[PDB]
Amino acid sequence: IIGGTESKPHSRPYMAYLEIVTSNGPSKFCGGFLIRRNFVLTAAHCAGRSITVTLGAHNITEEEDTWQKLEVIKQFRHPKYNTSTLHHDIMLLKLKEKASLTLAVGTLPFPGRMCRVAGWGRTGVLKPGSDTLQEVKLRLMDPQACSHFRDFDHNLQLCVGNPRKTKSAFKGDSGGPLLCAGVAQGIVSYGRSDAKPPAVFTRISHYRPWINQILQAN
Ligand SMILES: CC[C@@H](NC(=O)N1C/C(=N/Oc2ccccc2)NC[C@@H](Cc2cc(Cl)ccc2OC)C1=O)c1ccc(C(=O)O)c(N)c1
Ligand SMILES: *[C@@H]1O[C@H](CO)[C@@H](O)[C@H](O)[C@H]1NC(C)=O
Ligand SMILES: *[C@@H]1O[C@H](CO)[C@@H](O)[C@H](O)[C@H]1NC(C)=O
Ligand SMILES: [Zn+2]
């Protein structure tokens, strides 16, 4: 998160920190959020060979009793996920156990307006990931403001962030929820490599039928 501020610890108890393993290189990370005691929603571009989820964290380098470290047993990536057009960037992760509900861990059930995104991602173009969960408020834009992304499609995606400001999600914030009036409306998907807003978020409402079908059959 660029241009944001540190979240009050444990004030977003649905936030998941994801550590992604691949076979050919070192670990990477993304965000995501708990929608069921055993299901985390995140972006499909965070897929990997295996993933570990930390719930209940603030400072991700300081282990505490609120932590719940859970294994992911199966990744369900959207079947039409497309790395050419960048569409359908969405994935559910089935947890090996159901998470405990505590004060620090809980689920989040289901243009012009201000919304909030949160993450442990880089705080600057050339900066490391943040140790602590950060958040920022961002303006929802008319779809015209994302025209320069050639494969942007207003039906599938949200255009997020006022170009006149420097506030943005960045690397490591992938998969984090965009909340508008306490409801998850988007997931961080992609933007410019220089972070100039706006950025493109997955529009959660278009994928509700697909979410429901995975959650009902597992
Ligand atoms: C795990 C995934 C990996 N991230 C990553 O690829 N991206 C690029 C990316 N790919 O998006 C796709 C790809 C295919 C289909 C649809 C969307 N999306 C977002 C991105 C971060 C980002 C987000 C926003 Cl809002 C604006 C710009 C921006 O990056 C320049 C990212 O991390 C990654 C790569 C590097 C790091 C790192 O810490 O160096 C890291 N924590 C994570
Ligand atoms: C996060 O925790 C570590 C290890 O306790 C501490 O060094 C660091 O300053 C904390 N970072 C914060 C509050 O940014
Ligand atoms: C991605 O979308 C493009 C343009 O619609 C399509 O032609 C392509 O086959 C799709 N699938 C993959 C795997 O690129
Ligand atoms: Zn704590």
Image (tube, rainbow, N blue to C red):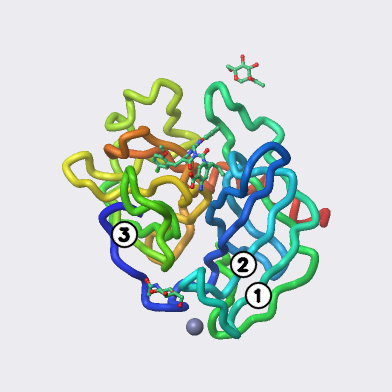
- Is label 2 in a helix, a strand or a loop? strand
Quadrant of the rendered image containing residue 100: bottom right
User: On residue 136, which mark appears?
Assistant: 3
Task: Please state the horizontal and vertical placement of residue 152, each as a whole percent of the image.
Answer: 43, 28
- Please give left or right for residue 164 compared with residue 134 in the image: left
**What's the CA distance linking mark 1 and mark 2?**
6 Å
User: Looking at this view, is 161 or 214 the one in front?
Assistant: 161
- Please give left or right for residue 60 compared with residue 210 in the image: left
Which callout, 1 or 3, points at the residue further toward the start of the chain?
1
**What's the CA distance linking mark 2 and mark 3?**
21 Å
- Please give left or right for residue 157 compared with residue 4 in the image: right
Tag 1 and tag 2, C-beta contact below 8 Å: yes
Tag 1 and tag 3, C-beta contact below 8 Å: no
Q: Is residue 154 above or below residue 188?
A: above
Task: Please state the horizontal and vertical placement of residue 185, each as a whole percent of the image.
Answer: 46, 53
User: On residue 54, which mark appears?
Assistant: 2
Which callout, 2 or 3, points at the residue further toward the start of the chain?
2
Quadrant of the rendered image containing residue 40: bottom right
Quarter of image, ligand 3:
top right
- Please give left or right for residue 177 compared with residue 55 in the image: left
